[PDB]
Amino acid sequence: KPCCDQCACTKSNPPQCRCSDMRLNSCHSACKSCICALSYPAQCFCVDITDFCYEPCK
Image (cartoon, rainbow, N blue to C red; front, side, top):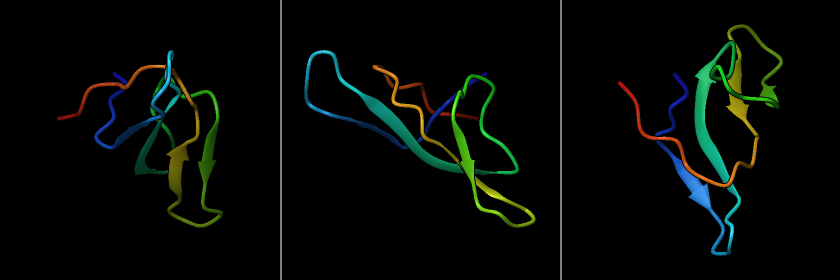
């Protein structure tokens, strides 16, 4: 499951939305571009800009 607690979206049709929340070692299953801190363990964000927000988690 890909979820997202912190979501962000530009006001526009359609909107580009990024997910700001930050995981360790890797991004969620449906993240194309994943950008992590070079360090163990690693702080990974998903920089994808999809045009809808995923739902929260847990």
